[PDB]
Amino acid sequence: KMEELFKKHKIVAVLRANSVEEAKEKALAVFEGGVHLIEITFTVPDADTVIKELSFLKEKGAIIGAGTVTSVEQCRKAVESGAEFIVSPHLDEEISQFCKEKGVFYMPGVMTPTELVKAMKLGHTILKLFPGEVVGPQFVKAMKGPFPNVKFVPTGGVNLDNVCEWFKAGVLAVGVGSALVKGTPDEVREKAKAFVEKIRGC
Amino acid sequence: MEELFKKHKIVAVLRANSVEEAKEKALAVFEGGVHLIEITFTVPDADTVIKELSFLKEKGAIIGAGTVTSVEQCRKAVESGAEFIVSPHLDEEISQFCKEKGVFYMPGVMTPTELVKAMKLGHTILKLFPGEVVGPQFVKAMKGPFPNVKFVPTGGVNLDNVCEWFKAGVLAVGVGSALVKGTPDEVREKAKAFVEKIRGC
Amino acid sequence: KMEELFKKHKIVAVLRANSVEEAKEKALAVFEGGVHLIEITFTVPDADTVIKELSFLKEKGAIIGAGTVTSVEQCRKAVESGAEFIVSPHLDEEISQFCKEKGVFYMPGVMTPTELVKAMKLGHTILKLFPGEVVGPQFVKAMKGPFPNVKFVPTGGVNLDNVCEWFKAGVLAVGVGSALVKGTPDEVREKAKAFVEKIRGC
Image (tube, rainbow over all chains, first blue to last red; front, top):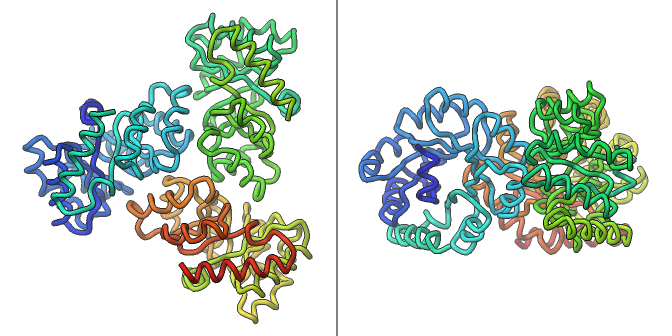
């Protein structure tokens, strides 16, 4: 289910905020601007409450998941609250096993070939590449040869200026954080439109 | 292998879409002066390719396997005559198998922590991958804390940067697409250029 | 205590050298130039001798530690010789445990988010980022989002040109090797003065 969605939409909003109220406002803005894939990070206070209270956005077509998951306890709260996918900055075998038990899509984050192979051995072929800015599109191109079956979602410093370079390198989708989600809701809505249009343009 | 890497300085990392293409490129490269030939397991029937190139060993070619990601692949490569095993990552299971089998294994590493784990498994010659991400800078940085580790970078090594890599302190380089892509004739020629450029530094 | 000393002093001299006498010459030079945090690496011959012999600087306010610690054996010798902190290029769980037991500050080095999370699970929030020149201040900015409580001390290529960029990126302190330590004692002392001024400035 999830693979096809990331393939279709090509962008996930990585939602960081300092309150439940701010996170909800930003999720709503990104969605109004055309971003349907929305990751509520666990750096948001009461992130699980946010996910539960965004059920109304799901009714409209939004796909709400959880990010910055660094423990199975957070993963469980995320899933119980309605998360449709789980993302972490790192590779975590425990979270991977939890998500399989629940039948929930997990996208671990990797930065190295060894992390990549460990993730692939746990059944993962769609990987978050984090921090993408640091390793660059070059990393994605380098992985093509040895790992033709693996697809990346680079996250970390993705912005309007570098988004097309990532798609030129062969990426499945991008995770956009601060370049998308910072600002007044009107600003965020218009940044969401800018990103959707930028991607449709590469 | 240590001494072979030291002497030859270049390993062709051979990716190809067929057995026939892989064999023709391995011959091209050898004819152009590259003695260390790594048949990656992304080559279809990479097993068969290594076995069918076994005769080149009699001409002094050293045929190994690359992109080895499981012990099952490792077994097939060794069974078919691979003289060395290379992977993009550090694999404890492949390390152990190659230790018992008495075959040289060069794991790939990208970080100081990965490097240290590989050293603890008995390795001091490491594939650095992807070289284009981490660069000569990484090789120079490792000389401080780990003076006795030596790297063989794979990834983006080309005619313009091969000498910088050797300036940074690498033991040999692994060259893929810059060497191996194109037709047999183009590959044999690019092989010659790399040997001369490397000798030239 | 070390967290507080890092924040106060902001720069650690990372001493590599080919002899005891060279290491001591460089330590004195850097100290006379106002760098109080001094890391003797275990690539210095008889580095534990260097640590013991520099003990007199401690009454002057120097804080002397050991770096390039790659085994518990070296860690035990360093602490025995008077090392007040321990640093490694990598994350070593055995060293972390030993240092925990002995009650000595340990700063493991990490280069990836997966290594970072493992180090956090071992109790570390202050991390060496190595090699700094490969991941850059962009790694430090990228980590602020998911790991807002983690503080970095980059080592690798920090120099007078980029030192303020690392601090502007959010680093707690910097580890400086050859940009600081290379040269005649007189040269090293003036570079130490230069680094302390430049850091105070930004």
